[PDB]
Length: 244
Ligand SMILES: COC(=O)[C@@H]1CC2=CC(=O)CC[C@]2(C)[C@@]23O[C@@H]2C[C@@]2(C)[C@@H](CC[C@@]24CCC(=O)O4)[C@H]13
Image 1: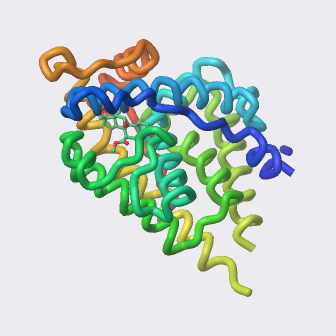
Image 2: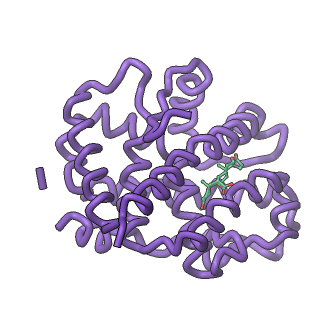
């Protein structure tokens, strides 16, 4: 099918600034609009990364779009946990160098509980001493973790790619290694529940954005308008390593 982990380490997207205006009041609307703007900028980086991801090009365009749209909150939250771990030892939420959340910002954002939920994942990175090589493979697995309930256009092509990256994770964890592999698959599975709550809040603010004064960039409007009716109608199928 394929040293893909070496390629993953090298294609990691660069630093994305939030463009946070600290001279503006820290209302929920101002913080959430900055977070949405940062998400749009990161989503362009996700598309550029995916294009050069080994095996991703073999999937038809429709499937590439489906995977990117279904997984955007997963990839985004996992990278946030990584940045938080690497740059603050998971003491804060490192959204961007110019936007680091402390307790004050967690409360002001009107997402305190969702923020604490995120902080728990970054705290697991500390507990496990997650490595950069493990992180990069796991991020690919999150891109491939949610599919249509009736499957993709080229389901066989997708399963081959996913299976091959799971094999890369197993080779990477290796004096006993099975223990580590299951610790990593348990972490990946726990992302689906967190992502459900994050999407619930995102969908809510999207449905009445002006009413709440929350701004969405064009990129997020497009993704969310497509994703929201699919997720809410049960057309999304989260893939679990270990059925709950
Ligand atoms: C703790 O929340 C988050 O951090 C997640 C993950 C994430 C990490 C990043 O590093 C980029 C930003 C995103 C995508 C995100 O902050 C934006 C704003 C999102 C889309 C939010 C879930 C709900 C919200 C709030 C307001 C809205 O409309 O939806 C995301």
